[PDB]
Image (cartoon, coloured by chain):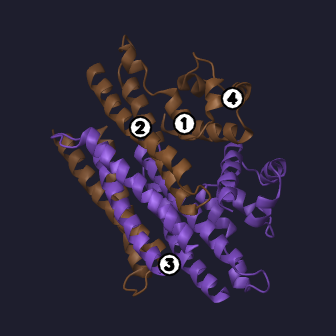
Chain colours: A purple, B brown
Amino acid sequence: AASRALQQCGQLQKLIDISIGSLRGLRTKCAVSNDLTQQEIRTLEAKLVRYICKQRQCKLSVAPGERTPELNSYPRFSDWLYTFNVRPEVVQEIPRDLTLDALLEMNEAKVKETLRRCGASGDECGRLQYALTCLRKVTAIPEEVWNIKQMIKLTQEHIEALLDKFGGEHNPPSIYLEAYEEYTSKLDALQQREQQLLESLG
Amino acid sequence: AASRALQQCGQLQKLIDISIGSLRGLRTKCAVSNDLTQQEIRTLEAKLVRYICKQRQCKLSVAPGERTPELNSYPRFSDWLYTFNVRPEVVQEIPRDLTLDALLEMNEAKVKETLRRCGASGDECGRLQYALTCLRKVTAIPEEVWNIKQMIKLTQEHIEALLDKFGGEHNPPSIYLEAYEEYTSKLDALQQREQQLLESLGN
């Protein structure tokens, strides 16, 4: 179990590193005051949180007894902080032995006071408090199978609704065309993943 | 301009209504403790915020003088609250004359005390405070043109990096395959929109 978990964290870390690069590019090379830039930042932040959660789940699936220190290093605290755009001068003022696992364990008043000691902004504290709540909520082929099937049904219904409201127009709005492309793509990704899960279950 | 802005708000509202339905389904028909469910909820919340901001931009691009009350009704405050999963018992305890435009005008202490008086949770107050900050940051064909071109370059680089790290594998991880599909799709959506913007800028 430890070998499989460490391999998965390493794969997840490649996605994280790529995504952190793209997030920095959106934040520095794009117009941040633009509503599409903001949508894409939020979407990439969401993927990074998912990848970080999956690394943590991989580490916790192993019984605690001597899961290799390489395995215990995932997820990386700096990756999570960078996901929520914590200023790098604040990351440098963070204690070395402090981990995301510790933040999850403290109460809300202690989290905020710890962030303030590092110089975190009031805007930065609410980000991480919200992030810990979204993180804590999350912390199985058949359970993944059922959930993916519900998500396919909703995605099919979303596409049908979009087509009902905008289909067959000769000057379709760009904002509709973006949703059409994304959701028909999402349906194909989900249907593919469902086949992967039905095989794993079978 | 009032006619065009109202028409755009109407199109945007159709996307909002559809998206609110899908968000409710994710929250009620799916496993909310699942990390893919959470990603998809976050992604739909992001689109909803974008649609609401675009409605607000449409209303504000028109000079204020007698823009029709139908136009002034966008965005709808309940749509924004539902996007951040505010409990309906809290929505009912919200004053009628209270608008999203007013919350944007208040200081942080005023926002929190107003939310608390409606019975909002501590998790709901920080959620909406975070939402107002993300909202306030946002609140033009050539500016859209330039931004899309930067986003295309990053999307292309993201795909190239995905293929560098995972391309040519015989058992590719599902999580990679999901990213590959999404980003190659996103590149096609961006490049199509770039064509549309280059046409509008041209004329």
Looking at numbered disc 1 in the image, what kind of residue is underneath it? Answer: Tyr
Q: Mark 2 or 4 closer to N-term? A: 2
Decide if residue A161 is on the left or right side of residue B85. left
A71 lies above or below B120: below
The structure residue drawn at horizontal position 48% and vertical position 72%, both measured from the top left corner, is B175
Mark 3 and mark 4: Cα distance apart in space: 46 Å
Dot 1 corresponds to which residue?
B82
Q: CA distance from mark 3 to mark 2?
A: 37 Å
Task: Compute the Cα span from label 2 to label 4.
Answer: 24 Å
Amino acid on which the number 2 mark rests in the picture: Ile
Tell me the subunit letter for badge 1. B
Which of B125 and B33 lies nearest the eye of the viewer? B33
Residue B16, disc = 2
Q: Quickly name the residue at label 4.
A: B115
Question: Compared with residue A64, is residue B108 higher up or lower down, i.e. above or below?
Answer: above
Which chain does the residue under circle 3 lie in?
A: A
Q: Of tags 2 and 4, which is closer to the observer? A: 2
Pointer 4 or 1: first along the chain: 1
Crowdedness near tag 4: few (<14), some (14–19) or many (≥20) residues, C-alpha within 10 Å: many
Which chain is mark 4 on? B
Query: Which residue, given by chain and number where applicable, does mark 3 sit on?
Result: A201
Which residue is depicted at the point 43% across and 43% down?
Answer: B19
* The N terminus of chain A - image quarter: bottom right
Q: Position of residue A192 (x, y in %)?
A: 38, 71
* Outermost residue toward the front in this view: A202
CB within 8 Å, label 2 to label 4? no
* Crowdedness near tag 1: few (<14), some (14–19) or many (≥20) residues, C-alpha within 10 Å: some
Q: Which mark is residue B40?
A: none
* Location of residue A51 (image quadrant): bottom right
